[PDB]
Length: 49
DNA sequence: TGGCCTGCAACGCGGGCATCCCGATGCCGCCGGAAGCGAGAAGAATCATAAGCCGTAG
Image 1 (tube, helix red, strand yellow):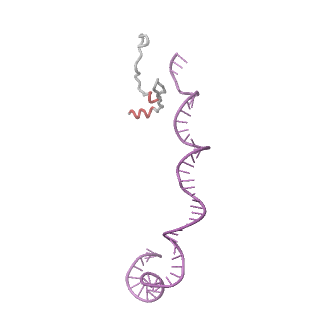
Image 2 (tube, rainbow, N blue to C red):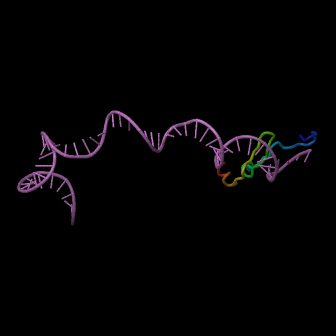
Image 3 (cartoon, rainbow, N blue to C red):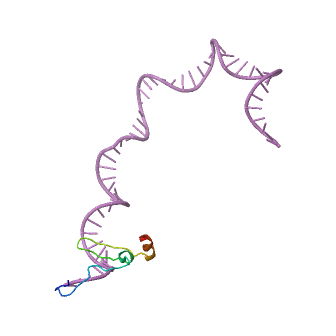
C-alpha cells in the first residue's frame, strides 16, 4: 500500500537481469555504507550458467 | 684424441742429533691514549586535527 492506503506498489520486480551486479549503486546508511563496481553482462550470464 | 697417474729404476739432499750463538719474552717499572657510555641536542617517522566529493534528504 501507499502512504495513505489508496494504491498498490509491487514489492520486488520480476526482473531477468541482476542489475545489482551489472550496474550497482553507491549509498550510505546512518552507520553503514556500500559501493559496488559495474560489470559486464555476458560474463555474469556465463557465471550464472 | 690428446694428455695425466703411476710403477720401476737411478740420483741426491736433508732429518735427525747437539750445541753455540741468538732472538723473543716474561717480568718490572714508568708513561700514554682511548673508552666510558651518559648525556645534550638535532633530524626524522609517525600520530593527531581540519576539508572535498561521492548522491539523496532536509
